[PDB]
Image (tube, rainbow over all chains, first blue to last red; front, side):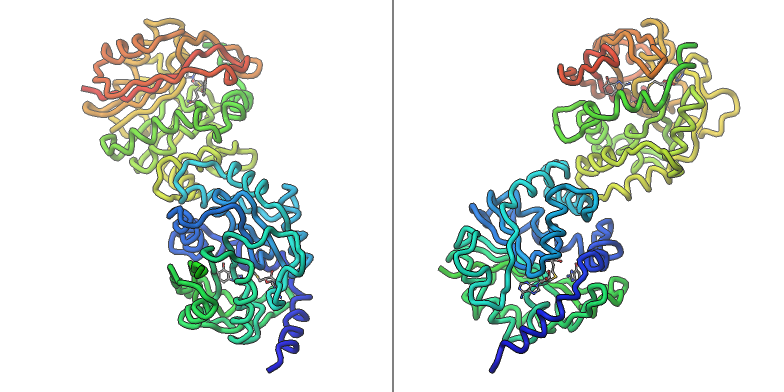
Length: 268
Length: 257
Ligand SMILES: Nc1ncnc2c1ncn2[C@@H]1O[C@H](CSCC[C@H](N)C(=O)O)[C@@H](O)[C@H]1O
Ligand SMILES: Nc1ncnc2c1ncn2[C@@H]1O[C@H](CSCC[C@H](N)C(=O)O)[C@@H](O)[C@H]1O
Ligand SMILES: Nc1nc2cccc(O)c2[nH]1
Ligand SMILES: Nc1nc2cccc(O)c2[nH]1
């Protein structure tokens, strides 16, 4: 059928996306409490840390797809990639990342995430060093639209193809349905070299979340749907794990039921 | 001694626990070295019990970071009221407290139990039952009817004895004095300046007895200790700051036998 109408709804909805509210809802406590090892924050960081710890995910260039105003997803990654591209649809998110890169006080504070990353990576690294490295390795912050066949546009800055991709809570949150999801997955997969790796994190069985005024629509997906989409896009699934959101982390900022983390290698 | 009546806790903290000496990023620094001696010792699981006393705490808490998870009853001490007030400010999370969070974080980092620094500080604050006045120069340093559970299962002291003793003999006696507080079989963890003769604390200028590693060893033996571990950290040039003339730092793990 027609993809344009659905995409236009999404783009419209995100014009009301408020980065601060979003940061507060997802990365401040209770969800942003990293003290409980059973929490979602620690689980995510652990998936990322353990994956990079295999040494199997490395190279020169990495691209973060739909970064938003967050950086936690790149904390463990930055030690393995000299060149990191961050990306987002919204200018206001790109600016938010701009505040953090300039180490402004106005910026969101990721230090609890940085510290927790250093802690689980087990190298005795101090968080200030972790943060300094990330800031050094982010070579550009780019506009992106995963719905376009060339999500970064034509003749764009990013070194292509990238050795690896990271994406957290993007696809399912900008895709009106499973078919749009699959197409978005196919588009970003063009940015990854063959043999490259994708690290994918997202909400399971979610239909909405709040970002200030904006109550945005999410395509509820299942683990098996995520798995099939990855296979469909030409990936071997190396790892796919599920975190079940505990009742007390269900706070009415969304209707998420769980979080998935996928490690996939693009067949080449 | 009367010199300690000019001792400024904020200036002391600033001089020794703010950068450069307070920068914990470089693993080769003295801060990380100290935390490591503490951490590694307790990790052995051989230094355990219910009660512990920190001798001459001053306005600092780093020395108990790893210790607090092995002892449910912790007593902190210092000769100066101003230091006891400063500790309380951090213990009660009052305003103007010193920020020990960099130290808490590195303790968690070093211990490697994936503990968050807020939990660490929470546990310490919880287990410190009391902050008592003390004079190591007295044969009963805590006094007659001290609220402190005696004898203690273990003792900790950092940069005290050598810093309040005019000379080696005085040093030795102060060690004998505190040793009476320690249950036989108990453990003492002792940290201090090596070959130091003075250090500043704002308007106060304190005299120190310059001691060597083997001098410390001998003193522990004489006091009735078996020396389990004794290590030295040589002070790098960039950590020589004009606030003292320390040459090194020692760590001793001693068991009362
Ligand atoms: N068409 C599109 N293509 C790529 N990203 C889009 C997009 N439309 C919206 N987005 C972005 O999708 C993001 C989802 S929120 C996820 C933020 C971040 N990655 C984290 O892990 O929390 C928002 O930043 C939003 O601006
Ligand atoms: N007669 C005495 N008996 C016990 N402590 C004394 C003392 N005279 C001075 N002190 C204290 O000894 C401390 C030395 S500085 C050490 C402070 C802290 N333990 C640290 O590791 O940094 C000061 O706090 C000082 O007030
Ligand atoms: N965007 C986003 N949605 C989430 C749902 C659960 C936990 C998280 O950290 C999330 N981040
Ligand atoms: N009192 C005191 N605390 C110290 C910490 C590190 C190095 C030193 O020389 C110190 N002296």
